[PDB]
Image (tube, coloured by chain):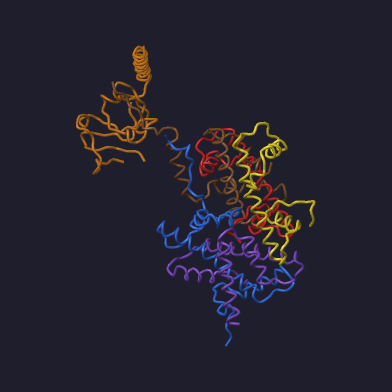
Chain colours: A purple, B red, C yellow, D brown, E blue, F orange
Amino acid sequence: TRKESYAIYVYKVLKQVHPDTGISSKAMSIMNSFVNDVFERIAGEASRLAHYNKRSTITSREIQTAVRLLLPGELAKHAVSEGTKAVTKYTSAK
Amino acid sequence: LRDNIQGITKPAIRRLARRGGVKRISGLIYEETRGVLKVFLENVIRDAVTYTEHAKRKTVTAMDVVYALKRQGRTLYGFG
Amino acid sequence: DNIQGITKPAIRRLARRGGVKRISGLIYEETRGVLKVFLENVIRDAVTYTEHAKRKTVTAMDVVYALKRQGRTLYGFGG
Amino acid sequence: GGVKKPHRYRPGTVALREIRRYQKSTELLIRKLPFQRLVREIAQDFKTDLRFQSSAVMALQEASEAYLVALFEDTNLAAIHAKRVTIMPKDIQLARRIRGER
Amino acid sequence: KAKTRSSRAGLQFPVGRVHRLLRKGNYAERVGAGAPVYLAAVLEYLTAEILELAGNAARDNKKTRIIPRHLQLAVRNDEELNKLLGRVTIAQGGVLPNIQSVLLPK
Amino acid sequence: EFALGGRCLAFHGPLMYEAKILKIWDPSSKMYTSIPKPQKLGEDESIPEEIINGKCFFIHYQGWKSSWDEWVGYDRIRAYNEENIAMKKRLANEAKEAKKSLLEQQKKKKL
């Protein structure tokens, strides 16, 4: 019965961006399926990379080689940058 | 039932083509298109009745439809 | 200029294998740019893969691997 | 003397007007019930008595109108390719002879 | 007192969830700690650029909420999000308004 | 005769046109009957005074929109009978002769 989805999380980041704007539920589902799909593509490529390099673990590195192999053009640079500063804050806060 | 392809009326095939930005639809297109709708809807629905049976379900689910569209490459957002 | 190394008669040979009987003259230089941008896509991914193995040399395996990503698999060179 | 003449937009004005009308609509075009039936007879051939949700149909449509409006779009470019504004069955065919379904 | 991993990373998307999923997804045998943090970091970005662009689209059509339509504009107007979401067909999107130059009246 | 919703042939310039009778007007009662019931003229409804003293009919031209709907008296309205249909054919032939004269004068203008 419990349905797991990214409802409140995308809503939060929406207010972080625009703390005045509503969202449609169908449009939400567009967002949820979209983040699920891009998550699948980034995680799959990563799994592959690993299996090619005879590794066995999905390091933050793979997710990068991946984000830079999937996300196109600039969308990547800004993804990397934000992912690197995010993992930097994760290791700084331990 | 039978021969309901004619339900995609010309008035509509046009409206779609009109949507697609065409201005003059030659006749002999209304038949071609319906044929294209029935090769697409075929494959998708086939890959959906295969998914349907695998789950031993009977009710073709919208969930299956989306997975089917993915296989062929035409992913659809808005349903799951 | 290494691009101009893809010579006309070579583009003509590609057209012949492609079944073209009369090649415009302005095609030759369009086929270069299209060629470049495409190679510039594979080789890019070929190298992302390369600098993931911390390898400095690229392999044909990484090349067909980048093709698999792009979509156009290549049989005959490994994998 | 002066005989009337009705106000008729010239061939193409009504066309482009409903083009601007329809390229702002997101509403589906092919009508629902007519489409729903399109499937029950396109499915009966793959499995009997396959029920269908009222969402599978809506999805299998959104996916269809989307597929068709794309193909028409490449059909048009293909029609303009021969310096013509009329689309032809060959166009839907050249287009599809290049996407690799044919 | 237990804090969440997202506040450790400074994110809004869940880093915890994206770990489970990564694990049960069996994308690979072992998953490290920083991999779900990075993925949540990239997903929120992509969810943000797309939401911003949707916000730029909506106000234009003077609509408070964000209907699925706006999400298409945002995606088809942008040339990056369009390569990404390029074989994707959003629900109730319509198409980018466009008519060819030869179809215009003289 | 004339009936509500029935066929009629009417003047319009020099030519004959088929029409539907939607309302029937009586000058004595300052009233008209309509089709989906006696009623008077509305706030925005009026009849030209040249015919309003005679028995009027609000008519709708076939093949033409509701902007062409108008009130006509016995001068401008006739019953739909074979005599009126025949003189309608005759005036259609007169319009055809006028169009032929148009063609002749324009082809002499080209020369």
Above or below residue A49? Residue F35 is: above
- Tell which of D90 and C58 is nearer to you: C58
- Of E49 and F43, the residue lying toward us: E49
Q: Quadrant of residue E16?
A: bottom right
Q: Is residue A3 visible?
A: no
In the image, residue D77 above or below residue E85: above
The picture places residue F51, in percent across and down from the top left corner, at 22, 29
The residue most toward the bottom is E1
Q: Is residue E15 left or right of residue F37?
A: right
Any part of residue E65 in sight: yes
Q: Is residue D70 left or right of residue A18?
A: right
Q: Estimate the x, y position of residue E98 in percent, counting from the top left.
A: 48, 45
The relative height of residue D70 versus residue C26 in the rendered view (above or below) is: below
The percent position of residue E34, horizontal first and vertical second, equals: 64, 75
For the C terminus of chain F, give its image quadrant.
top left
Above or below A91: residue A25: above
Does F14 sit left or right of E27 as displayed?
left
| Residue under the image location 71 percent in, 60 percent down | B57
Residue at (53, 32) in percent of width and height: D84
Taking depth in this image into account, of E97 and E102 the one nearest to the observer is: E102
Looking at the picture, tell me which residue is in the foreground, C17 or C12.
Answer: C12
Which quadrant of the figure contains the N terminus of chain F?
top left
Residue F106 sits in which quadrant?
Answer: top left
Q: Position of residue D68 (x, y in %)?
A: 58, 45
- Total marks drawn? 0
